Image (tube, rainbow over all chains, first blue to last red):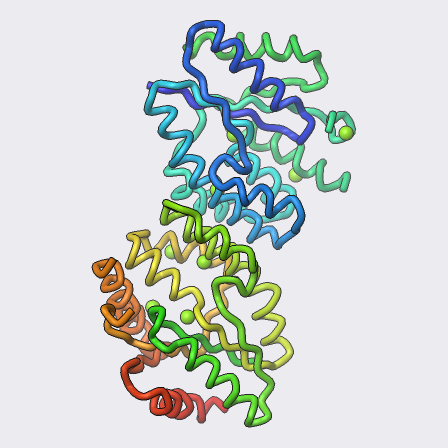
Length: 185
Length: 183
Ligand SMILES: [Mg+2]
Ligand SMILES: [Mg+2]
Ligand SMILES: [Mg+2]
Ligand SMILES: [Mg+2]
Ligand SMILES: [Mg+2]
Ligand SMILES: [Mg+2]
Ligand SMILES: [Mg+2]
Ligand SMILES: [Mg+2]
């Protein structure tokens, strides 16, 4: 009986660091953990390809969906099956925020593509590290659409999303994630 | 206006030879033609990703779709918009026969993915080079072969099914005769 958790937000919102800290917290409790990430957790070559080329949004989404399809089947589901807590730095919500709200693809089609790609795997909890694009540690209108897109997703699924102020000190954010998670272990 | 034609079949069916002979034939009639193909017509590098070992049928389809989405947008639709005859050696039916009939993916999901990927662009005619599957595992290739025949039965106006074991020049003459009314 595994537990699937995801972290979401702009690049530079603290995803990595908080994924790393949440893993250390679970290691400290003796709970087996698997840290992973998208894009590249399924097809690393999708990540590298897309560093240097820009494609239509449709094609970008489909490449990311291929990668996600492999990631789910070869990494996440097997980790869950072994009773691990599997933490993904980015998952489907990234595509919905970036390719959907950001680049304007229709959300119902994105979700229908995803339904087979993910085999319907949804995280139990998703932590959204929210901040404005100007506060991210690592064009402007686009990033605002993405940030507001994540907030919209979060509003629609208040039982799944936990929204944190990503401008808070690292350590504080980590303790809030822990408090949110304690009931589910 | 533009005219969109595709060729389909198993590898070794002759569909590539016929697509090339068709392009030459239409260009020798002074017709503007654009010859393209999948995979790789949209995203040349897709061919690398498709060679990935142990690739899931879903991931394989999604990669072909990503190429296909780029191919439609950047090559095919602009070609048609300039009034070219655009001929693709393989198009969406290849995925339906290989990833659907061959690898078992559900057709309705394949189609729903395809609806944005392709922007609903359908060929006017599709020439299927029907090749017995042993001439191209074997159980997989039978499924793909029969799948193509099913796709053809389902859309008998679009598909022209040709016997791929006929001499090349007889096949080309048959393709030409199917085209003469639209040209
Ligand atoms: Mg997520
Ligand atoms: Mg997806
Ligand atoms: Mg910034
Ligand atoms: Mg928005
Ligand atoms: Mg497709
Ligand atoms: Mg076709
Ligand atoms: Mg459908
Ligand atoms: Mg059909």
